[PDB]
Each structure stands twice: as structure tokens, then as C-alpha cells.
Length: 128
Length: 131
Image 1: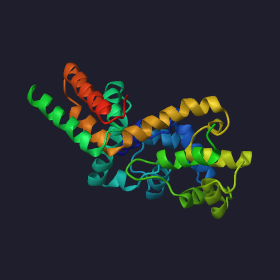
Image 2: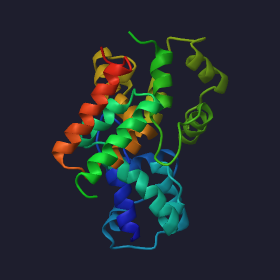
Image 3: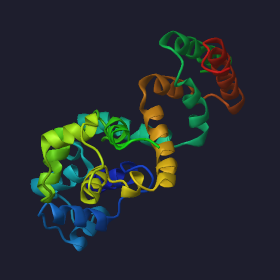
Image 4: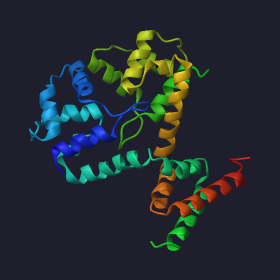
């Protein structure tokens, strides 16, 4: 996956409660406050793929804004490991998965093991 | 109704980045420093322990801003309600156990998933969690 896709993936998956995805402007602004200068056109270009190969410092500033290791942009193994965590940040906001998953919070370790067992049974009764 | 220490500690406990754990007090001190905002490390420890209370407006702004939430969370008691529900979903959905269950139940048809939920409800009544 490209820089643009990884960058945009952070924009789409990493953000605060009570609101939605960060905007490019919020990022330019936050960088400004740490005394870092980045142009909106440049950020835009990085997001769109009209410029590529961002410098180590540009990458470290974007990674610091989202609060993740820069290795996310440059290392494939780590990218995938962390992308799994981001994936969950999506599936968790699902309403269908909230229903089930949620009520299980509150059961003791032992009782959750029986839920896992019931699930395995429903799996076989289907595929799977 | 919740004190200021409880609302702050909740933020530490539930709001942190993917692929790691809760932020530490020092991380917050560090960050504000990078923004040009000065805050005392032992002071912060006392807001958290409730030794000191009634924070200044500017103090609540700096902290809210770090966690990237509206300051109204500490003041406007109705917004605190709205948000603490979302925080509750965060704590809930990032818990390993619930996650192991949701990812295993994922892919089952709608009718089978209603069944997983029925078994959860049964154990909750049986463990005394519901009554």
C-alpha cells in the first residue's frame, strides 16, 4: 500500500470520541502549534498522490499528530500489525457487533469461555 | 455530579492511541510543553488524586485539548452525559475479551448471532450481572 493510502487510512480510522475524522486543516493547525510548518497544498498533494515520497520529518510530524509510530509508513510488517488494530476501530463502531460484543463485557473470564464455545457450535452448524 | 478527578482519570483510562495503552501524566506534561503550555507535573498528580480541585478554566482547556475533547465535558453536565456514553463504548469495545468474542461471532448469519446474544443474556442472569 502507498503513502497516500496509509495516510488517508489514519484520517479515516483514528479520531476522538464525540466527533468524526480529523480534517487536513486541523492537522496543519496542530502542527503549527508545535511550531511546525506544513502547507495545506502539500498535505493535500500527499493525500491525493500528486506528491509522493514524503521526507522523514514530514512523516514523523504526521505520525506524531495521529500518535502512532512513523514505522507505520515505512515498515510493511508493522503497518499490517497496526492496521489490524485500526480495522477493529471500524468494526467496533458497527451497530450489529455492538449489540453482541457489548453485553459480554461484564461476564467473568469463565463465562465468556462458554460464549466462545456456543459460537464455535453455531459455526459448525453453518460452515465454517 | 462526577468530580473533576473522576472525569480526568476517565479520560486517561479510556482515551489513548491505537496499538498502545493509556497515556501517562508525564506524556500530557510533555505534550503541553511542545504546544507552549506550561503545567506542573506534581500539580497534575494532585488534580488526579483530588488533593487539589476546582481547576482554572485555562487548565481544563489544556487538558481537554490534549485528549482532543470539548472542555464542556468538565463543565456542561449534559454534554458530559452524551460523551461519557461514547467513552463507555470505547472502554467496552477495546476490552480484549469482548473483542475475542466479536471477532469470532463475526461471519455468523443474523439468526445465529441473535443466538449468541441469547446465551450471553442467560449467563448474565446466571452470574447475577442482570436481575
